[PDB]
Amino acid sequence: MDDIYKAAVEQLTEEQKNEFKAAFDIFVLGAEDGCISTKELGKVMRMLGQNPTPEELQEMIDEVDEDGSGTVDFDEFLVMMVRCMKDDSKGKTEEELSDLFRMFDKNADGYIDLEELKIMLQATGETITEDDIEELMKDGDKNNDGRIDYDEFLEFMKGVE
Ligand SMILES: [Ca+2]
Ligand SMILES: [Ca+2]
Ligand SMILES: [Ca+2]
């Protein structure tokens, strides 16, 4: 990978720059020149949704910083917001298909039934009839409990339609 930390920095968009300039201008509150030591960076972590300690950020600055002064800069800072993917609990593949569950379920009954499936068919431009709905729960259902569920739609989305 041609520079994984400097790539995002050197490749900054003008839209995210106007947002970092303000967020970065607050992290330097109390400092002298306009940077962040460790306690000032604690506010940067709280933004995502975490309250780490100022002692754990110090060891993280020497790995991102490229000078050796013991402080973060407008450049070494953006690097910290690049190594963390945009997903703390989510992931991919099996996590990307779970999104269909929302549009598939309507009242959180498990997944879809004879009345809920009518919405998943209307979203598709394909022509749907009454025989296509009764067939959806036929092979689409493995337990035949009356509706479907994430465990069933998992294989149903393996290229069936
Ligand atoms: Ca530095
Ligand atoms: Ca439902
Ligand atoms: Ca079932």
Image (tube, grey):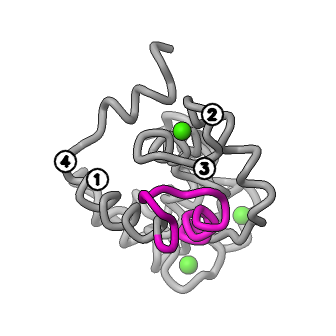
Q: Nearer the viewer, mark 2 or mark 3?
A: 2
How far apart are the alpha carbons under marks 4 and 1? 6 Å
Residue 86 on image: x %, y %: 52, 50
The circle on residue 16 is 1
Q: Residue at x 23, y 58 (%)?
A: 18
Q: Is ligand 1 closer than 8 angstroms to the Cβ of mark 1? A: no
Q: Which mark is residue 68?
A: 2
Q: Which residue is mark 4?
A: 14
Within 10 Å of disc 2 (Cα), the crowding (few <14, some 14-19, many 20+) is few
Dot 4 crowding, Cα within 10 Å, few <14, some 14–19, many 20+: few
Between residues 83 and 18, which one lies in front from this camera angle? 18
Q: Quadrant of the C terminus?
A: top left
Inter-mark Cα distance, 2 to 3: 40 Å
Q: Mark 3 vs mark 1: give the one in front.
A: 1
Is residue 139 visible in the rendered image? The answer is no
Asked whether residue 119 is drawn in magenta, I would say no
Amino acid on which disc 4 is placed: Glu
Name the kind of residue labelled 3 in the image: Glu
In percent of width and height, residue 84 lies at 58, 45
Sequence-earlier tag: 3 or 1: 1
Disc 2, ligand 1: is the CB inside 8 Å? yes
